[PDB]
Image (cartoon, rainbow over all chains, first blue to last red; front, side, top):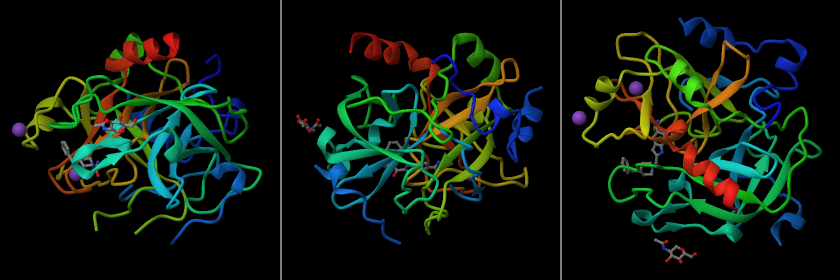
Length: 28
Length: 12
Length: 250
Ligand SMILES: N=C(N)c1ccc2[nH]c(C(=O)N3CCC(Cc4ccccc4)CC3)cc2c1
Ligand SMILES: *[C@@H]1O[C@H](CO)[C@@H](O)[C@H](O)[C@H]1NC(C)=O
Ligand code: NA
Ligand code: NA
């Protein structure tokens, strides 16, 4: 899909969920 | 607990 | 999910619930990969040792849900299945190798703030993100503990574990088509998926394009959140060729 993986209530609005920083911080 | 009744249209 | 937390609204718009018609009950998790295709674990539909063998007419797919038991009027969409495809080489007799299945919806579902497909990984994304130490996210309405049910969707973030550690934690023969995830007994953090969560997605957020990719499918484990044991997931990229084949041909 063209816009797969981009959530309307989060990425599309530039808002982050409560714990996604945890994932990103683990990607060295 | 148990599940709530869903519309009959989805059971036929 | 064990030791997780309630998910925020719209946090996993690709999460799908596999619902049994009669008796009405939750069977497993699943994920939306397009407007007409759902991805899940084959053992959710077929597992002969437990006399389990569901067909298209036996169940429903419920999308856009948050609450586990309520019929979320005007939010969720309930779809009927047109066809189920189980991997030709799904190994239910021994180790659940290739525990994957595709389900074709009778009609496309409209997307919304609560319903949106997840991306399937490409070789580069998989090679870049599937590494020991890197965390993924699992979601589901499954059991909260080995031995009850949550009120709303649960979520837990878990690190991918080195293959040797995965192999040395079980007697089951592990294949290239699976990976395991979870904290080690000494890491002072817990969490695992559990019964009812299988079929659900293990996703990761790409730091390159900000998209969420489904790297795994909740497959199996021995117990739930047991120290020294890990959750095992079907390797989605490893089986992508079969996925594309089914979608393209059918
Ligand atoms: N802790 C976890 N991560 C976890 C996640 C999903 C699960 N599903 C089942 C379950 O009910 N299954 C049906 C019976 C199967 C028995 C089995 C185990 C290993 C190899 C082959 C079959 C396991 C899956 C157990 C289980 C444990
Ligand atoms: C499962 O159900 C189907 C009905 O489609 C049947 O054809 C098959 O023999 C059953 N058993 C297995 C192991 O597939
Ligand atoms: Na072993
Ligand atoms: Na564990």
